[PDB]
Length: 90
Length: 91
Ligand code: HEM
Ligand code: HEM
Ligand SMILES: [Mg+2]
Picture 1: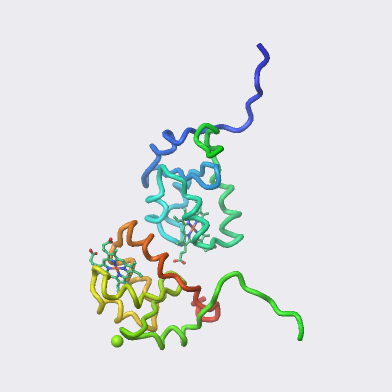
Picture 2: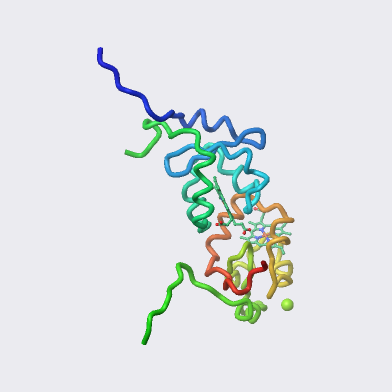
């Protein structure tokens, strides 16, 4: 009856996919979930390039843009949890 | 013979971009990046002239005002050739 200790909060992709609009947008980048709602209208690349990646892996999109170190550091403020292990590639 | 610094990406100066302003060779600047669209002119659904009209200048607002689809934005990546030189960016 020993129990695994919990640490990070996991979200399944099907739950992430429900926050898919200007009301509330979560994005998945490198295995982590970011609630970027508050940043949508500040994002230099605009809202639409973020919105269109709802519910899918946004990592390739994010990396192809060539985001600066400053942009990468801004990521952490929007962190809310990790994608559930069952939704990752092995 | 001395130390030199290197950049991550390939840069093109706006002066080099502005020379490719025709059907023979057309480059565009969209969101700080340079695209060689010569081979796409003929197939572009919005026609050739709206692309040719943006030679030599920043085409970002024109591209954004059209409301291009996600497919069109992914397609834009196929034409990427480099980033605009840092010295050509507005403050
Ligand atoms: C999710 C957290 C994100 C943050 C904090 C973020 C942050 C930033 C920042 C600060 C810039 C300014 C340039 C730089 O510093 O590199 C930028 C530019 C940009 N971002 Fe993001 N970004 C995020 C996600 C994304 C995603 C997912 C996409 C693509 C689907 C995207 C596409 C772009 C584009 C296209 C630009 C260039 C804008 C231009 O100059 O017109 N970003 N981003
Ligand atoms: C290499 C960069 C470009 C690509 C890949 C591209 C791609 C496309 C595609 C695929 C479409 C069909 C509709 C859609 O899927 O959104 C389209 C339509 C259109 N494009 Fe572009 N385009 C580019 C640059 C531009 C630029 C710079 C302009 C403006 C000067 C422009 C103006 C238009 C117009 C007017 C339409 C048709 C009207 C529409 O349905 O909104 N495009 N473009
Ligand atoms: Mg001309």
